[PDB]
Image: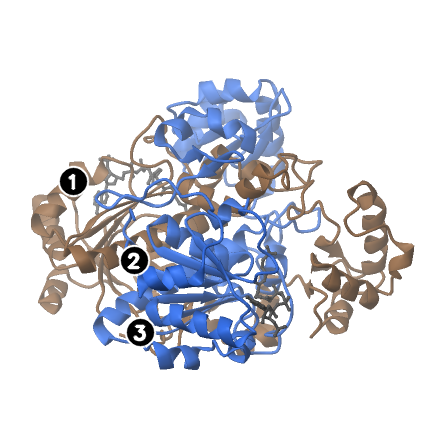
Chain colours: A brown, B blue
Amino acid sequence: MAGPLSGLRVVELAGIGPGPHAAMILGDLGADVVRIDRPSSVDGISRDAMLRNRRIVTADLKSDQGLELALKLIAKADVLIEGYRPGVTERLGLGPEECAKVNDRLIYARMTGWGQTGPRSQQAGHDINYISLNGILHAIGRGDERPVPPLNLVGDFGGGSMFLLVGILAALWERQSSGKGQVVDAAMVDGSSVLIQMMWAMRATGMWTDTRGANMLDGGAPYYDTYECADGRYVAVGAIEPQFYAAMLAGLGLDAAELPPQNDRARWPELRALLTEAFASHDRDHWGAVFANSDACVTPVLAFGEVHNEPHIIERNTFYEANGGWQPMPAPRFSRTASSQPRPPAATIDIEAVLTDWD
Amino acid sequence: MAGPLSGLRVVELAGIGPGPHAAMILGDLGADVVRIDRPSSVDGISRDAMLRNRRIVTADLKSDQGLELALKLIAKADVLIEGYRPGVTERLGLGPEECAKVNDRLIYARMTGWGQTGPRSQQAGHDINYISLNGILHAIGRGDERPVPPLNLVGDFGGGSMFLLVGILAALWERQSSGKGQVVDAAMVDGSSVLIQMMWAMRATGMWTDTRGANMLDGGAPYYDTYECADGRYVAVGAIEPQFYAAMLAGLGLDAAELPPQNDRARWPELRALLTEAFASHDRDHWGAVFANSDACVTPVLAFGEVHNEPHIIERNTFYEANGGWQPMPAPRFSRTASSQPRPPAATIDIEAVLTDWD
Ligand SMILES: CC(=O)SCCNC(=O)CCNC(=O)[C@H](O)C(C)(C)COP(=O)(O)OP(=O)(O)OC[C@H]1O[C@@H](n2cnc3c(N)ncnc32)[C@H](O)[C@@H]1OP(=O)(O)O
Ligand SMILES: CC(=O)SCCNC(=O)CCNC(=O)[C@H](O)C(C)(C)COP(=O)(O)OP(=O)(O)OC[C@H]1O[C@@H](n2cnc3c(N)ncnc32)[C@H](O)[C@@H]1OP(=O)(O)O
């Protein structure tokens, strides 16, 4: 199996959102990932590209046979991933303490939103809930409107699966001294809070306020925002540094002497009005040309369906084609032990066949 | 030094955004992290909490002595992090090949937005630019408005630092088998694409559209969005699963029989209006009480300044008091080798000291 995690063995108790995303990435980087789903489920080969780089197996974990086979897989593996509510694996007989009895090398990775304990620890939730409690959601969107969810990128993935991954891999490094596994407790409410550490840093030094839409990086700054062009499509401007901002102004045709200072916040309304009228005067693809190879920090805001036509995307093979759609190639990239193209979802395998393989 | 990464040595070439965030998380988990800044920028003790769990040293990397001292660190280290444009470390004489001469075990980690090669590889940029090219930014915000940046959470951190960490720690695992380092190439345009793999998966199966504000998780669904309350504050609703949705309706006082179907998208505007009126008739904290211990997936949207007073946050110690204010405690969490509270940024030390300390 190609990639730096060749030889790493992972058991994933099938759930939704962060658990499978983390499992995907371990698979992507060469891990041997076996996913146990319920029989009531799997009516064919999966159509869900997120289940790439998997072997799927079926097993009623409520039955004693189910549990036994499961504990035999875990015995032969380096990592377990579960993202059920706290208590669920315990009650199945697949809890950490049970796992520690058949494999004290196990990295026992627990993916939740609220964490393992505390008042919300049994409440159902999704991304939007976890980021609502720690200040993140409130910071996202225009100042004249209610907050807008940043899809499920910040709680589920950035602050969720990715922290689970770092935990697993950090724990494997620990396991190199100690010869012992341990439990990784990844909660979206915690990981997302470390994800936004910069805002907490800036808040402390007076460089970030709680007012939505009134900061340097939330859309409040005219030089860090999107602009509507003549065709109704958009560009993004990120020209924070003064030298990049000056480069942007020259490409737009605006003389710096006729504008308010870049960082005179009291005159941001005027500045925005000027930049707005300028970008509105030509179409997105015009601005893409003007600013290609410039440091002006102006880029076209492409829709998903146009991404496959962008030269920089094509040339670095950020994406590959698979069963009626582009999908992203593994990230990040490795010079010597490169990942390979992901293996698509495969039909279910037998749990005995797998135990054989793992010897 | 507490945490799973005790004994890991990291040299960080000072930069902005994702590199410092990665180095911070490594530090948080107990890595020994030495950050080389330039003499010209360091003054007092840094007031940037992102620089916690560091030793800071200065050095003109353009001098003969600075280059030498730096190469002697890297000789003794496990990982190097740099986040300059491609070619920059090569020209300083700190490129991968030069480092491979003095330490074939080094994990050489390169954090960029656009990657190591390709047409955009020398273009200045910020988060908003990287996420504009791969479809992410276009998908964020309300449908009748221009896209809104989700701060710098998705390119810099979620698809940036976190992928640099996954690559560093995966490469360390590969090293245990191979005896050798390698180069990790973490590009924000790639990582953020993998971060949003769920949308590409959903797009392939006809369950995600390129129309902004018309999807299950972008704010277009009335059961996955924020709602303004009687007091002008907000709740988040995340009631995707029909059973949680039913529980929310009961708590709102709304008879399901009176309402359009949860997932009849043609009638979402109509459903939204009914839910809007309901949420508007009481204040945020009222809804917080009503739905505590519920699976209705309704949570108060707290501003940063309110987070310190939420019971669930307090009791799990998601934050600690610092210097200027509250900061996120390390994530994720480890049962056996737990992280300690971060060490605040401490004054510049002398590079020779570190070399003594390390050899
Ligand atoms: C993309 C998205 O929408 S992402 C979801 C975001 N949330 C999270 O993942 C955080 C994790 N915590 C949670 O909130 C939950 O996982 C939820 C809310 C997503 C699901 O809630 P629930 O449906 O109550 O599931 P919960 O995790 O509590 O339990 C799963 C059940 O399946 C059972 N189960 C698991 N695997 C199997 C199996 N192979 N065969 C049979 N039963 C099984 C468990 O034993 C449990 O039954 P029980 O609780 O009645 O004893
Ligand atoms: C918070 C935010 O907004 S963060 C996200 C920003 N984006 C990225 O990080 C992507 C990757 N990095 C970059 O694209 C760039 O570093 C930018 C766009 C951020 C800034 O561009 P530049 O200012 O041109 O920096 P670049 O990386 O090209 O080079 C930095 C210079 O610092 C110099 N330098 C670095 N360390 C030292 C030192 N200790 N002493 C002296 N000089 C030093 C380098 O030698 C280089 O000099 P040179 O090109 O003049 O030979």
Q: Are marks 1 and 3 in contact (CB under 8 Å)?
A: no
Position of B295 with respect to A67 (left or right) is: right
In space, the residues marked 3 and 2 are separated at their CA atoms by: 18 Å
Q: Are marks 2 and 1 in contact (CB under 8 Å)?
A: no
Seen at 12% across and 59% down, the residue is: A76
Same chain for mark 1 and mark 3? The answer is no
Q: Report the front residue among B217 and A181.
A: A181
- Where is residue B326 shown, x and y percent of the image? 49, 34
Residue that numbered label 1 is attached to? A92
Label 3 CA crowd tier, 10 Å (few <14, some 14–19, many 20+):
many
Q: Is residue A162 visible?
A: no
Residue that numbered label 2 is attached to? A169
Q: Amino acid at mark 2?
A: Leu
Compared to B310, does B263 lie above or below? below
- Where is residue B71 shown, x and y percent of the image? 42, 73
In space, the residues marked 1 and 3 are separated at their CA atoms by: 43 Å
